[PDB]
Amino acid sequence: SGFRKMAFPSGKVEGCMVQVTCGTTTLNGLWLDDVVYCPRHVICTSEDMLNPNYEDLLIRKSNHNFLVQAGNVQLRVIGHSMQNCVLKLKVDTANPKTPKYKFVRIQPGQTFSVLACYNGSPSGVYQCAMRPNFTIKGSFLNGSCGSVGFNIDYDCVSFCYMHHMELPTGVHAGTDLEGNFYGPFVDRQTAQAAGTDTTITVNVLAWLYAAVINGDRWFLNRFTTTLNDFNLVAMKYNYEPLTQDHVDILGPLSAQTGIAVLDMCASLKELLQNGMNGRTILGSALLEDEFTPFDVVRQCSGVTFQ
Amino acid sequence: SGFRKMAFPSGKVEGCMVQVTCGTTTLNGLWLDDVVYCPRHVICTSEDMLNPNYEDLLIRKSNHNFLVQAGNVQLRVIGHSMQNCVLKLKVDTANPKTPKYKFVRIQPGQTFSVLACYNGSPSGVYQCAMRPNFTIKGSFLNGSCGSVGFNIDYDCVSFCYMHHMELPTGVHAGTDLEGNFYGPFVDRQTAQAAGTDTTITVNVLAWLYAAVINGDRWFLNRFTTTLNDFNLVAMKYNYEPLTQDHVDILGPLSAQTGIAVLDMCASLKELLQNGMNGRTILGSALLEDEFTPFDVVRQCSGVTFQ
Ligand SMILES: *[C@@H](*)C(=O)N(c1ccc(C(C)(C)C)cc1)c1cncc(Cl)c1
Ligand SMILES: *[C@@H](*)C(=O)N(c1ccc(C(C)(C)C)cc1)c1cncc(Cl)c1
Image 1: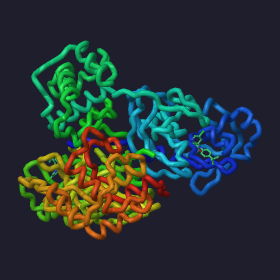
Image 2 (image 1 turned 30 degrees about the horizontal axis):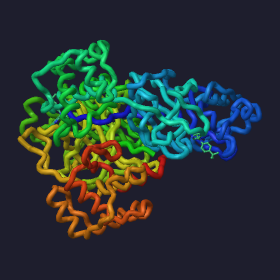
Image 3 (image 1 turned 90 degrees about the horizontal axis):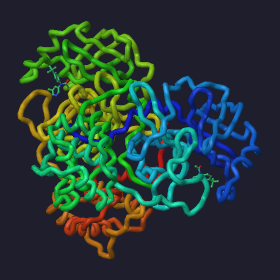
Image 4 (image 1 turned 60 degrees about the vertical axis):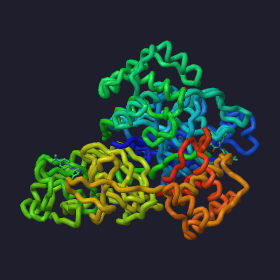
């Protein structure tokens, strides 16, 4: 029992983190086989970052302008190219610690682990969700760009996020590992802003099931609701719609607890309309939406990775 | 910016996790140099665990009764001994992945990272605090005993916790790495129970400072309080007393924010007496007490580890 914001073990990613320096700009890179991936804004300067012409900036660089440090060992750069908003630095050494990996792009509502890094050195690990508005509520300081987000499935690391920037509300934006931004953000200094968010309804329901599995049942009730009637309430509280596919994905948790999905929707409806009245659920006084149905099954059943 | 429950990178500990089997009982062990450490209740059987005589049980075992698996490689046991509530299995191979390490015992109120493991394979990582009542609110399923808790300081892993059991309220008890239980718990099946807990006042204050550093200021006020007058309120809300040493430890955060410690105590007092009135602090609707002043400085300043 218990229920925690649980990240994947980070060892496989730690062995891929390096430091990339261009000029006086230093950030994190990801070393897989003989390529180092990093944000292209490593080639910018204080005045460049207003409205940079990255193609122009890059043609003016040479391999020797990029210093890559893997621990206390320097990696000779032998080639460079731009792919969307990431740089690909070809180095003369394949990373012997390269795990089996994939570059995957995730959906809003999906979760991943972040290995926050500074100067190529891992600092901490935590779990994040991709918000509906394509930001993430991370924890990042200056010099963290290039830190990556990932999931692990058995032995394979699916990289899904590379950190680039902080938005004015303190949330974070970045790209997939092909360099394509999540959401309507650009790697330059504009007035860009996050844009309105919603609550991830299917995840809230998954977390209520986690709570029942763990013995919190006070919010259960005898009522039920229809899917359409629930979605009317969801819209009014800024929750996103629940679909039949969400209902289906919640099937296993429904079957394990014996609480019909639409019955749990009725419970969520009451919680939205009445608040929590001084009580908590799994140690939270808020409805938590950064656990997917998979996260709940993983933690309340116990899947490992090797 | 941002503020997350952030664990240490787990790679250095992942390389130490092994599977220990005795009879039909399988759990996790920690392999450092040529010793595997694991809970002594690996030698128990369904009927043994009522009131086991562990000295009796152990004299009846041989080295060959212990199978240690490090991944898909079997470690030959060449010696065994009991140290309090842990077993020390001498193996014929020193772990080449042994980090620099220490065995430290922590104080209630202190935090650490847990690498949850099953069958010697890491499953997830999360941050925990030692409660005042010497339990931890972990996330553990059957087969997790032997998973360890730790902190990392530069390159050195300070192991502080080995998981043994779940108490009836769903919280967790275990030992330090010398086998000495945290709190009044025993590795047998009795009616033992957690006992009354309190809230870690100095940590709540640290987290309020984290919030101010991150731009949540709505709970600030012009009032101040004396240390004695604050502690009268703390006692009434089941918070533990604040000492002058706590005030001193909060000095740096006080100086960074310009909010006197006793001024933040006045804010905490109002929050305890009035609740939060529908607002949140760092994404929580509860006063959070599992971040130490060190955790706040680490995350709001950015210290790495190598
Ligand atoms: C990601 C990153 O490193 N970065 C950044 C680049 C350059 C500098 C100067 C040293 C030239 C001031 C600082 C930070 C960055 C962060 N967020 C957005 C953008 Cl466009 C770049
Ligand atoms: C830690 C652990 O493995 N364990 C446990 C031992 C033995 C068994 C049987 C297979 C013999 C039923 C199950 C679990 C354990 C957990 N919590 C408390 C105690 Cl005393 C032992």
